[PDB]
Image (cartoon, rainbow over all chains, first blue to last red; front, top):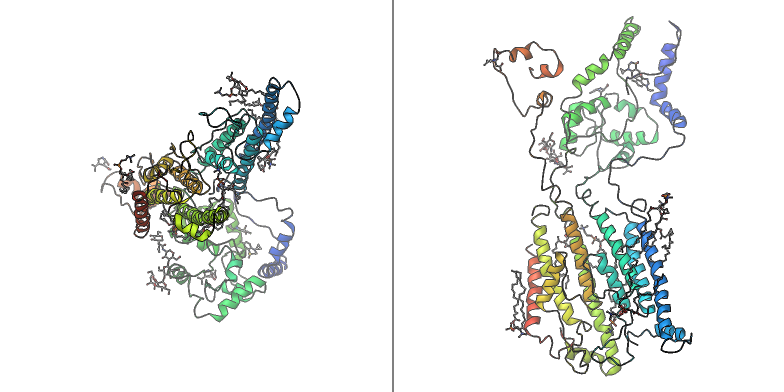
Length: 117
Length: 309
Length: 152
Length: 32
Ligand SMILES: CCCCCCCC/C=C\CCCCCCCC(=O)O[C@@H](COC(=O)CCCCCCCCCCCCCCC)COP(=O)([O-])OCC[N+](C)(C)C
Ligand SMILES: CCCCCCCC/C=C\CCCCCCCC(=O)O[C@@H](COC(=O)CCCCCCCCCCCCCCC)COP(=O)([O-])OCC[N+](C)(C)C
Ligand SMILES: CCCCCCCC/C=C\CCCCCCCC(=O)O[C@@H](COC(=O)CCCCCCCCCCCCCCC)COP(=O)([O-])OCC[N+](C)(C)C
Ligand SMILES: CCCCCCCC/C=C\CCCCCCCC(=O)O[C@@H](COC(=O)CCCCCCCCCCCCCCC)COP(=O)([O-])OCC[N+](C)(C)C
Ligand SMILES: CCCCCCCC/C=C\CCCCCCCC(=O)O[C@@H](COC(=O)CCCCCCCCCCCCCCC)COP(=O)([O-])OCC[N+](C)(C)C
Ligand SMILES: CCCCCCCC/C=C\CCCCCCCC(=O)O[C@@H](COC(=O)CCCCCCCCCCCCCCC)COP(=O)([O-])OCC[N+](C)(C)C
Ligand SMILES: CCCCCCCC/C=C\CCCCCCCC(=O)O[C@@H](COC(=O)CCCCCCCCCCCCCCC)COP(=O)([O-])OCC[N+](C)(C)C
Ligand SMILES: *[C@@H]1O[C@H](CO)[C@@H](O[C@@H]2O[C@H](CO)[C@@H](O[C@@H]3O[C@H](CO)[C@@H](O)[C@H](O[C@@H]4O[C@H](CO)[C@@H](O)[C@H](O)[C@@H]4O)[C@@H]3O)[C@H](O)[C@H]2NC(C)=O)[C@H](O)[C@H]1NC(C)=O
Ligand SMILES: O=S1(=O)NCN(C2CC2)c2ccc(F)cc21
Ligand SMILES: O=S1(=O)NCN(C2CC2)c2ccc(F)cc21
Ligand SMILES: C=C(C)[C@H]1CN[C@H](C(=O)O)[C@H]1CC(=O)O
Ligand SMILES: C=C(C)[C@H]1CN[C@H](C(=O)O)[C@H]1CC(=O)O
Ligand SMILES: *[C@@H]1O[C@H](CO)[C@@H](O)[C@H](O)[C@H]1NC(C)=O
């Protein structure tokens, strides 16, 4: 605040009401009605709080998009495990005189999960 | 555990469970990971795969923590999974250890009260005002809910909490556990000279001083003029800055050296010891699953345990 | 050697002696760590264990100092020991190297008062001039706020 | 420090007595 001022019910110069408004303001202030009326009008939308100088840990807003490039690297990799599956079955044709059940019996061997064979 | 938010510590921990299940599926699916063991006997259809569900999860945890593991991936397919999990855990740690500099120097405790609401509900902290003042008389003639409970406390204890002056209030804040209710232009003077004290909460009401004159004096319309003149000239602020400043108390706008201790890092010796008590429950748990499968090959699973001990 | 307190440097050094003895007991106790050597001759009851008391202590020191070692653990049991010692030494070093920034400087020993303003508000530092000089007489006949408190 | 260095000393004596009394390669599976 640059200075300190205040409002006030203005009365003419020498009115008998300024000693009755003064009483009726000091009565409303100790009853808490001058604060009750100010909270009724000056609140409105309580526009959201600032989260000043404190910690500011890292969230999805800051780092965030590495879970994109993590998930974009795994969708790339499942395109390659298929791409290795097709280059292997193409070179399985040169010993088997292409069958296309070669790609079946190969993906049978995927379901031979036994740490071996 | 602070420099990453508690949704990031869940997204990292779901990524280790995520990638290791993705790495295990691709390793069993890819035909180049199925290498042929026994190079001494290179003629048998016994091609094996080293990626278990164990070893896939301990390539995910082993590369999360910079030490690395066995089973480097051997494909164009499983090395894009492993190669992108190395770039993930590079940045997560480089974001962690570059933010942890700010969270080892720190904050302190916050007071048990923060307003007159929190101070009304507690019996643990006694509190009073000056007897025959305008602060006591405020709570005496009030009828709002919070500020009448604060007078229900004082009227029962008028020989104990209601001090006789502002100086007996400040000393009982110091020497005891006490929450003295003083007017806000005295708190601004005391809490700059003393650095032990603070102002809890905002202003309860709004009041003001004033040169008192007798009932109907001709001076109150001349003092009023001579106050409003001093206020626009800036002398009522110039006098207040001459007295209420004093020692302009800081403490902690400096934040010096502060080596780490058990107070700062401290609780990793908890999660170290909580990980070893977990592990001795598992070495027993492997002992019981082995002896249960020893009951199949042989007889008397209990004495099959006793021989190997 | 300052950014960790001298009880933490003792708790770290007891943890290396702690975990490596825990890792050596579990590795000899677990039946999956006892792998079979000689894969060229896969028929003999000569199953071995690579975790000695040497190699258990040099998985504890080798993972404490970020370089890693031989003998990655091979179990569900010895990899929870090794996996929690990797998370321990991750944080201890990340707490060390994020605090060591403050202890290679400090801010090289400045003065408590830096003007006549800071020296006016303190009673801790006494101060005076030469009696019957032109410095005393300056503060005697002054009326500016700071330089009158210094005459008070 | 006074208590836990005794606990580590317990783990150190056991780890020696396992190391001395055991042929780590020979036949001996599942022991201690
Ligand atoms: C292996 C491959 C893995 C790939 C996975 C990750 C791939 C990326 C996954 C997700 C990315 C999500 C993109 C955000 C949305 C699109 C906008 C955009 O494209 O940005 C801009 C291009 O920016 C550039 O100019 C840089 C080019 C892209 C990076 C090069 C790829 C790295 C390949 C690695 C080589 C590997 C070999 C290295 C050695 C191993 C264009 O848009 P803009 O208008 O200029 O900016 C406004 C943006 N806004 C609209 C959002 C506000
Ligand atoms: C950041 C993004 C990635 C960038 C990286 C790019 C870098 C260039 C990447 C690869 C370059 C390849 C160089 C070949 C190696 C030379 C040796 C040789 O001649 O024999 C090889 C050819 O025998 C095969 O069967 C081919 C399989 C090779 C691995 C997969 C590549 C082809 C995938 C096809 C489909 C792709 C799908 C594409 C979809 C669009 C065999 O070698 P091996 O298989 O290793 O096994 C034997 C091991 N040994 C040799 C030690 C004994
Ligand atoms: C998922 C499908 C992947 C498949 C395999 C997964 C298996 C499991 C493996 C890993 C599991 C993944 C981690 C688990 C938790 C998810 C992370 C999270 O919570 O939020 C992340 C969501 O980001 C994503 O998860 C993907 C969203 C789609 C990507 C958008 C661009 C498309 C590029 C792909 C196509 C290119 C193809 C390749 C191009 C060469 C953060 O993003 P955000 O919150 O939305 O942003 C913040 C916005 N905010 C500020 C408003 C808050
Ligand atoms: C990537 C692998 C999986 C990761 C799992 C992640 C688990 C965490 C998930 C969520 C954490 C939140 C819930 C924990 C319980 C809450 C209690 C609490 O506040 O902390 C308490 C316990 O804290 C711990 O001990 C940590 C939990 C176990 C970690 C060690 C075993 C798992 C690591 C190996 C994983 C192998 C197992 C996996 C399968 C074989 C500590 O506080 P206190 O003891 O109550 O009081 C101390 C007194 N004092 C304060 C005065 C000083
Ligand atoms: C905190 C959790 C535990 C709490 C319990 C507390 C008390 C503990 C009580 C008992 C402990 C449990 C049982 C005792 C262990 C015996 C099992 C066993 O035999 O292992 C075997 C199989 O094991 C597997 O196949 C599964 C392992 C893959 C997942 C790894 C755990 C991480 C999952 C994350 C969890 C979710 C994370 C969510 C985080 C919020 C390992 O041996 P093998 O593979 O057969 O040998 C290789 C075969 N070979 C020789 C041919 C080469
Ligand atoms: C085979 C036996 C294996 C175990 C031992 C193997 C040897 C290990 C090798 C070395 C020993 C370990 C580290 C070195 C010494 C300890 C250092 C220390 O400071 O104490 C720490 C722990 O100790 C405590 O203070 C007790 C805390 C109670 C909970 C601890 C969890 C353990 C139970 C597991 C629960 C089951 C979980 C199951 C899964 C969920 C913490 O101290 P503090 O109290 O936080 O400090 C006070 C803070 N203050 C000053 C600010 C007030
Ligand atoms: C500066 C800090 C250094 C710390 C290092 C401490 C850890 C490492 C310490 C010692 C490592 C243990 C040695 C075992 C070696 C195996 C050899 C064997 O098979 O039989 C040997 C029996 O010799 C022993 O087994 C001695 C073991 C008893 C004492 C071990 C702990 C002493 C504590 C010390 C202080 C504790 C406090 C630690 C913290 C200060 C005899 O055989 P060999 O003649 O030796 O020939 C070997 C070759 N060959 C078998 C193939 C033929
Ligand atoms: C950190 O904060 C602590 C609590 O927040 C605080 O502890 C308080 O210390 C005072 C002493 O200064 C304790 O007072 C005692 O309680 C009775 C109550 O009747 C006192 O009468 C008594 O003697 C007083 O002591 C004064 C100073 O020694 C002295 O002027 C008089 O002799 C007077 O009679 C006791 O000393 C109080 O209960 C404590 N509060 C607690 C334990 O909650 C610490 O002082 C504070 N430390 C610092 C460095 O700031
Ligand atoms: O204009 S006033 O009557 N007199 C000046 N002041 C105080 C000197 C700050 C104040 C302070 C608050 C007011 F509401 C009114 C006045
Ligand atoms: O007691 S007063 O003279 N009149 C009432 N008020 C409260 C703002 C209502 C105020 C506010 C600030 C004052 F400085 C004085 C008074
Ligand atoms: C110290 C005393 C009695 C005075 C100080 N000013 C207040 C007043 O202006 O009446 C009183 C304190 C109070 O009631 O909190
Ligand atoms: C040595 C004395 C008393 C003299 C020297 N010149 C100043 C003068 O001529 O006033 C004084 C120093 C001072 O005021 O600190
Ligand atoms: C309170 O702060 C002062 C500094 O103004 C300090 O000297 C004192 O030790 C602190 N504590 C107590 C109990 O007075």
